Amino acid sequence: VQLVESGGGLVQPGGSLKLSCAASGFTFSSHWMHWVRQAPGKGLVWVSRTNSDGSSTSYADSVKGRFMISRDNSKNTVYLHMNGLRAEDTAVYFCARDGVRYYYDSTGYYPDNFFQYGLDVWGQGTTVTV
Amino acid sequence: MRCIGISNRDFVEGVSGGSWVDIVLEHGSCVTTMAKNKPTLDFELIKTEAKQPATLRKYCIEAKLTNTTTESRCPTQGEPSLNEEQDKRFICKHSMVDRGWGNGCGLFGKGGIVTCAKFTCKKNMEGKIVQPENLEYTIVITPHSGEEHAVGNDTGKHGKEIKITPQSSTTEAELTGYGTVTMECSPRTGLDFNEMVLLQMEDKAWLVHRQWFLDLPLPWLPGADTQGSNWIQKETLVTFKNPHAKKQDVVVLGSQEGAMHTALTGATEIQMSSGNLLFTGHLKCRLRMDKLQLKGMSYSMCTGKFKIVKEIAETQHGTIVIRVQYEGDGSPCKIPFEITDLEKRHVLGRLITVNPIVTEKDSPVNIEAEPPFGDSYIIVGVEPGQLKLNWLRP
Amino acid sequence: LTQPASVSGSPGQSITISCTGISSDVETYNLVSWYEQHPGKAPKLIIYEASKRPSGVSNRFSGSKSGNTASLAISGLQAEDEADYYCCSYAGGKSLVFGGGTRLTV
Ligand SMILES: *[C@@H]1O[C@H](CO[C@@H]2O[C@@H](C)[C@@H](O)[C@@H](O)[C@@H]2O)[C@@H](O[C@@H]2O[C@H](CO)[C@@H](O[C@@H]3O[C@H](CO[C@H]4O[C@H](CO)[C@@H](O)[C@H](O)[C@@H]4O)[C@@H](O)[C@H](O[C@H]4O[C@H](CO)[C@@H](O)[C@H](O)[C@@H]4O)[C@@H]3O)[C@H](O)[C@H]2NC(C)=O)[C@H](O)[C@H]1NC(C)=O
Ligand SMILES: *[C@@H]1O[C@H](CO)[C@@H](O)[C@H](O)[C@H]1NC(C)=O
């Protein structure tokens, strides 16, 4: 049950960067995937979420407009598109699997309000400096 | 001299000398007007422009669906609702989906689903209503001033630019050194803009029947809402799909650009060169050479010898152009010119560039004349050193 | 979501970590989530659905739900529990928010 991450490195302000999160050991197509930020020495910040196909997406007010989530069930990978990156967006981005929702929605599609979640499996993360 | 080198060149001359003369101007046409004791002029319509267009509607021919939002409720939990529903840039639709234990509902039954997507127009067409009287015409009046660079010079400001509307047709144009020519025009468009819409599509345009334009099944914005966001009839290019009561999906219908062009076969097309409109129709104009006068005429003939500074070239109409420089003294001067037979007996062939004069010695003069068929002699200057040049014309 | 800055407690002692942040709906607090993160390392789900504990997580870890508060209890502190604890819940029906962060000092 792995969650590999890639894309981090040197990034100039107001620039484009795509973060890829690989997956194995589970029915990825059937799970809601999440992006969670964390500053060098600070707290967790939830960034984005995606349902099975990518019809239901959610973003933090802090990233709304400049960020974009996407995924292809073929490659079993989730992506985070970050355009116009401001200096305050510097952090270690994490991709997490909402495993609890699977005990409730075996499809991982249905965009319900306040459905039971629980970010089960987490990746090692990737540091970006802007 | 601007017309020299144009295929569709019309040589027009007045009756009973040439006080007045009728000319037809069109895009691609060029007219050389001649009147006795009056300077030869070149007229060319270079621009046609619809000047006060009123957008009726603006149609979306290429649509893009972005920012997709979906919300669902369990059975006996109410109709779902998104704030994107009230937003007019979005297109929403509700449906019913089978809900159970296996998909996250405590009870089995139909559960409400709602999908919303932002409608963004990629490519569009516009329908402008043009008042016929508001069509501005730009005509260049280039005299036959022998001028070194005059001959076919498109940009170098040799001719006077004048603007005409079907409304304001009568114009007096001042040609420096020649006087004023009066133009009474009359446009022969071929097709009026009565119950016609000028349908503009990027670089192409058409003239279409009003009700037909107002009946196209495409998303549209009114003339009142240009740069607007709320596109009416988004449904004409957006379709919702839910055939198994499992998931609702939004789908576009693809670019109607090509589809449109096919419907616009039985429509009058209008072309565009350098981003401006080229109306197929003619333009009849009446001229008045009454206040026109030849530059000089009160001058004395050239005492000195002439030098042919450029090889005689024949135009597509059989006329010839000759560039000659003055090596003598007397400038401002008057060039002696004649086309005769092989024994100098009779003066044959006419002169297109009437009253050829030398202003500055250093500046060459371009003389255009129609030589007769067969064998002729071009005679430039007076004795001694008279330029004798044999000409061939089958 | 406001969490206390840091909670200190002796080994053997039982403590509790609060979590409260403006939201006026039972849909929020009944769905609080707790995460255990050691420095540099990746976070770990210790409590979901306010009280539910996943297999692997020690018996000592408890999950409480108040009207407008959420609590994480560590009944019997051990040296190994010295880490960072973050609560989490729904901002809106389709949105998640993490708490301030509590630094557990054994
Ligand atoms: C179409 O028309 C063009 C412009 O229209 C006409 O321009 C004038 C000349 C009038 O006829 C007027 O009725 C029209 O409005 C026309 O371009 C013009 O052509 C001349 C060259 O024939 C341009 O350059 C000028 O000539 C000298 C070259 O000098 C040598 O040759 C002459 C003989 O040709 C000898 O007398 C000398 O002793 C030299 O041996 C250029 O060097 C110079 O241009 C440069 O210098 C000036 C002054 O410092 C600068 O302002 C320029 O920018 C240049 O760097 C002369 O000015 C003349 O520039 C040009 N006019 C314009 C407005 O551009 C063109 O030839 C015609 N084309 C066709 C295909 O019919
Ligand atoms: C919609 O998504 C696109 C692509 O991520 C983004 O550029 C745009 O700003 C979003 N829409 C709004 C209303 O901000």
Image (cartoon, coloured by chain):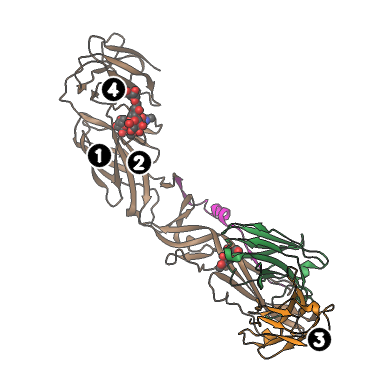
Tell me which chain the residue with mark 1 is part of: B
> Is residue A84 placed above or below C78 in the rendered structure?
above
* Label at residue B45: 2
Say which element carries label 1: strand
* Residue segment shown in magenta: B247-272
Tell me which chain the residue with mark 2 is part of: B
Looking at the picture, which amino acid does disc 1 mark? Leu
Instruction: Say left or right for B201 vs A55.
Output: left
Q: Colour of chain C?
A: orange
Question: Is disc 3 on the same chain as disc 1?
Answer: no
Q: Quadrant of residue B311?
A: top left
| Pair 3/4: label in front | 3
Looking at the picture, which amino acid does disc 3 mark? Gly
Residue A26 locus on image (x, y percent)? 82, 68
Alpha carbon separation for disc pair 3 and 4: 123 Å
Q: Dot 3 corresponds to which residue?
A: C12
- Cβ atoms under marks 3 and 2 closer than 8 Å: no
Question: Is disc 4 on the same chain as disc 3?
Answer: no
Alpha carbon separation for disc pair 4 and 2: 26 Å
Q: Colour of chain B?
A: brown
